[PDB]
Image 1 (cartoon, each protein chain N blue to C red):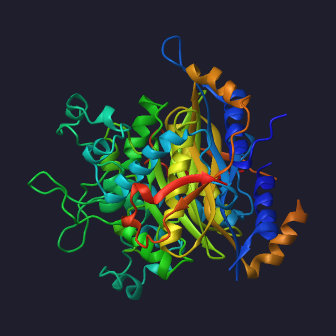
Image 2 (tube, rainbow over the protein chains, first blue to last red):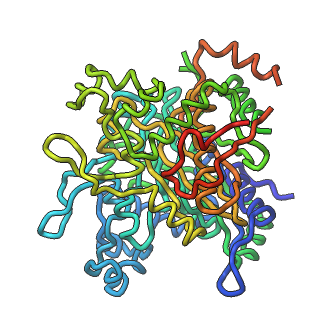
Length: 275
Length: 260
């Protein structure tokens, strides 16, 4: 029998649960889904990094995307300069015109929500810097008040969720400190368990390690919580294949220990190595 | 079955909870099938009256406590005193941008005198329309969390965000609670949001599915340890009854809502 490591066991348990117990949606046209509403998985970050089924080659793009969010940038050029294509589909002139904005501009996606939540718009067409820098506040609160029960970052502004191609699926996240270890929980309103969930878990587990380092903490658990948690019917066979695949090796994150500032990480500071 | 999920949470915190006094876990989830009965858990029938009136107050978008005080519901009084409101430059009885403001007027701007314009986002009105016209939407969401305002109120919203879901004409709801005292807060808040789910289901012509409770910082105070331990040994869900004539989420009155 295949003996999967803990993180992959939890992920495969989710795939199996959706395949076997998910409710059916869709009619006679268009790809259907099986889904459940409400799911939760826990990953002890001291027991390996939860890369799950993410290919190591794609980890590069996960890192660069996270650095882009952390910079507060919502223009695609930084990603394209780094050969990361994750957001290209929604940054074409055709796609940005759907929201009345210029090519390369994604609108108020994660970077804006994280670094400038609720800012107002200037007559020059850009955001004023009068929003709320949730990342800066968070780091300061962890350092000065680690027992805070509101170490929260929200990606959700209802006035703006309808003004982007993909209303933020990584909707809100929260941190927690216990025994000098930093834990994080992500609330994901919508989760494609096959194509999206592994990447999102890797992204937020990475962020947890980065914040832990700059605050002088160890890592606790990453807790993944899903709302509409679904598997598209064109992936049922591929999901069944994943369930029967040989176990993947454990891996661990290695961060440049000299980085002391959450906004000072570069791509080369972050790597995956053997456990 | 509803009490079993809740007793399992108590047992989990008692056994594997970290100590800081309080024992606490971070990240937990419970599911209640609303077709099996109303999850009143340990909330006494006396508290149900306050749960109902408070929820109607939230839905009105009111953040002045007058409506609560008129109805003998004092749960917000400690934060509505002149001394407490003065901390934020607000008149007596004005709590500022608490739940009702977030639900009905998220992100609204202010006049010079501190009163809000109604230029924010009415999440409740949008939600009702979206359930009726697009029930498979994956963003049937109400957020209580504005970072610009969470530090501008006495109690940053504990019921941080909630989401709905429709399957087979049954409405489910998931609550994200950033912080929760398991002994009193959790049962009260489960009842509040399960009630809301029933009210929204009725106005949209739907049945009820599950209520999913998700906790962030989930804690038990030391002064409740012994009571919690004995609650596991004690080992009878009620039923909600709504006036079937109410077809608008803003039209429920206290008299329309009963627990049998």
